Image (tube, rainbow, N blue to C red; front, top):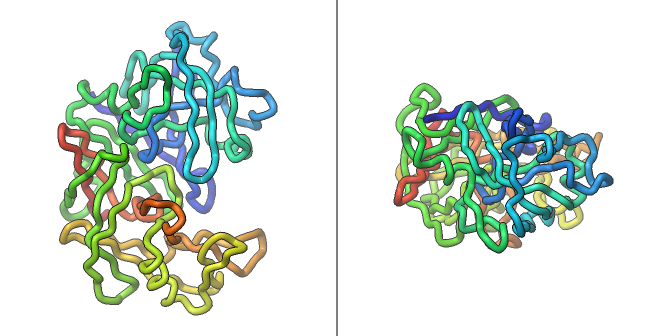
Length: 330
């Protein structure tokens, strides 16, 4: 089997992407944030504290003839941005772009933190990291990809995120029309539960490439590119007036600037992020200070190849017995 679904930016900055997902019988369609940095499929629901729902579409398990309470199971998750959610668990039928999994764990939110409530466009998350990170207790549950894998034509999914435009998540096949050149594959460590890999270095604008190993994760659920302080300083030094602002929470730059590109290495291959992809707009409405799309990871503990980096590439998440990642230009 295969599936193919369009993913759409939630706003004019590409802060996140939503993909429609069918849950239950008859189908209830929710727009979920596909997140290769986590491993829980959770949704706003008829059980979510009413004051914490503000415009989201909810899953109502009592209206699904295929929903079953997973008795005794609870979940609770905290994300790198400080947001969180928790609740109980049902199993139900879940379809993405024509690909159907029966018996998928659908984690129903009883509580969500303020940032989720405040984002009316995201009805939940669909985790695509390794199932060892799933938070369901006392019986850990499998991701949608893990449950679908054996049925897929090939045990892969691909992320093709757009810049200020829709893109595609495919399951079970590699669309050879969606990229240019060849796909370069690179080793993955699953030891932390992430799609963790080592970039071979970087360049800033037209500058020379610096060969240096940068370990990080391919994370569709993180907006920006978070890299070591040395790398980030070298980038922003090329932008007149750019500075790190403790009050704003990162590097800012004059909105009048033209940003240089940023290149990262994948083996001997190179992915070029255009300068425009690094502009996240005014820090507050009407400001002439703009927020940068490359930020330091020094306070995280891990480097993160988020949407800023991934949307410059066609990315293969290869879930074979030994997983690997592939990157192509597009």
